[PDB]
Image (cartoon, rainbow, N blue to C red):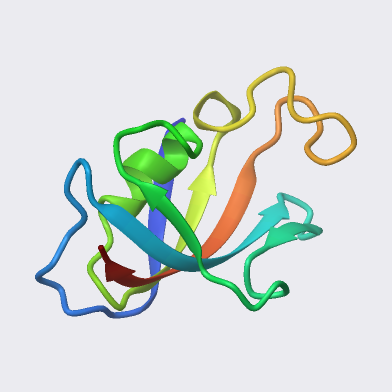
Length: 108
């Protein structure tokens, strides 16, 4: 599968990230069993990435683009849209479906 987006709290429902814009997010990343492997919130610093530059996984590129500014949403990302068969040694196992809690704070 690709990326499924499930809303957690609504944004403005009007402003959506466009290619080339910087997305400022807080996020928490978890394996399918629920184990947290990454979280910008634990570092108390929002994560920024530029949409369309493939600085993030494909599930992020296509999933965050579906979110409006101020929205919090749950992205469930299949391995093809994620770290694939290889995964990430000692962080993400092979063929892993990942669940991201993502809040889109603003666009720059």
